[PDB]
Image (cartoon, rainbow, N blue to C red):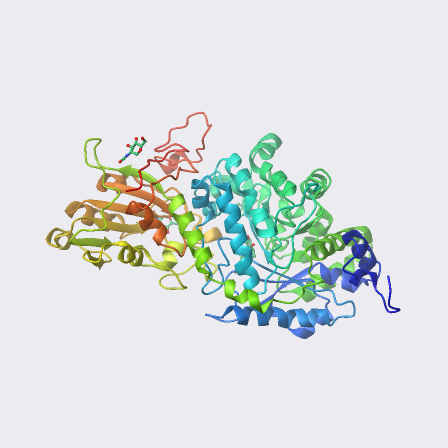
Length: 606
Ligand SMILES: CO[C@@H]1O[C@H](CO)[C@@H](O)[C@H](O)[C@H]1S[C@@H]1O[C@H](CO)[C@@H](O)[C@H](O)[C@H]1O
Ligand SMILES: *[C@@H]1O[C@H](CO)[C@@H](O)[C@H](O)[C@H]1NC(C)=O
Ligand SMILES: *[C@@H]1O[C@H](CO)[C@@H](O)[C@H](O)[C@H]1NC(C)=O
Ligand SMILES: *[C@@H]1O[C@H](CO)[C@@H](O)[C@H](O)[C@H]1NC(C)=O
């Protein structure tokens, strides 16, 4: 269809399947295996991308061009990499992926949304789709096309360091939150075939249902460990949200580090090929986790040859190498050349990677759009996040006896009030993990509003606000305070650093709460990624709020504390009495919760 140098794969009016086949039929083995290779930006250069025909780049946690980098600096990095890839013989654009898992969270000045567990508390799948929408805009502002989200793990033991990344222990709630997908990607059209990949265009991003499958079901919530459960439990708890993901056209699926009844997920041909591909009819691409194939073996990386064979034969399409790309490429090339991996397996992986790239419009818009840069940290999106933070809060207690005046909502006018605790004026702590750094961080790491700042912004001008991080009891008693807001809880963590067998918040926490509440009527805001031991915190407090990891917009906290909106959130998990009860989930036989799933007190706007 027209000029004499016409190449069908480059014709944007042809059907995606036609473009895929046309390109595929021209590629060498080296160009094919290059598509299946994703590398970290830290090892990428123009010659490496060009000479190995690389298919994808990512930024892992905290992998950034520099600290404080603008949206424009991100776009230029990405475009730099893309220009190298476009200069190959076939000019196959790369796709760049990142963990935008509560906003575009590696990026300075990006809106940071509440983490998933909070989002579960809102029971509001439309809110979540809207967060999808806004997140895609902030991701594209940085020139990125691909977000490794949502995590649709069903966390079954809060001792897991990734429990905050799961919407709920109830798979019904996780299923309903897969609306993040069409938020990120766009609504699939009228007559869409379930399992097809979809992205609407250059203002949307490819998504990633992760981590397939049973990541949330591991023994004692040990991260990357074994999930021991029969097929029926696997299918009825851990799988259903992947099917909803198929119906919404999720573009990619990332495989889990975890194992199911002893089999590494990265080596499981039955689940990856037999079930995801052949039974759910997934036509997008399947990507490893970060050195996921290495960890097939014990020790990890001790037989990389096997790692490659097993993972690729299992059915994985793209490998998040992400550093030793030369070895990965050499090994896979060697296995194809020796007939150990058939060309049909290679052609299938490449067919899928290209399908996603063509379908999302990457060949037509390989480069970043500088007018999208101003979407980073947009106030409209912060106002959404603030809404989400407010809706996520669960009021556990609001008065020490059923006869006391309720403490919340608090009046904005009072001569003098106290704000206290390690989490009252600490942005990093209120964002938690996967914020600027991989593990999150402490203090003022990005743009936002801490609890203290939000209080100051909310109160009557005549109200005197005093901050003290960890005051003693005499300070409180002597201070002439009308009430106190005290914020404490967990430090930021991510993956295995967060695995925790005791779930007790660090000190000082409880002792500040005791000191403060012993001198004045107090509202304790508890910041955590999960239920933690809370009886002592309850005994001391007039009111206690479980605010999860609410993100950059701390005004969502005060919106509820001061009565602009009523508390409506409900526990998306069971709150245990004791860690020895664990695992303990709603529907279990000796369900003995401190607070059951669904619990939450309410208030009315004032
Ligand atoms: C930087 O991402 C993380 O980096 C640390 C730094 O050492 C690695 O050891 C971690 O295992 C990865 S975790 C893994 O990364 C994916 C991409 O970052 C992510 O989508 C996935 O959910 C994680 O399990
Ligand atoms: C589970 O964790 C232990 C360390 O506690 C490790 O030795 C074992 O290999 C892990 N199993 C799996 C399947 O990851
Ligand atoms: C609880 O467990 C974590 C390990 O994840 C540890 O850092 C902390 O010191 C422990 N606290 C108590 C009270 O045992
Ligand atoms: C808010 O409205 C509910 C429903 O009628 C009511 O039960 C609750 O006690 C009210 N609280 C107020 C006005 O403080």
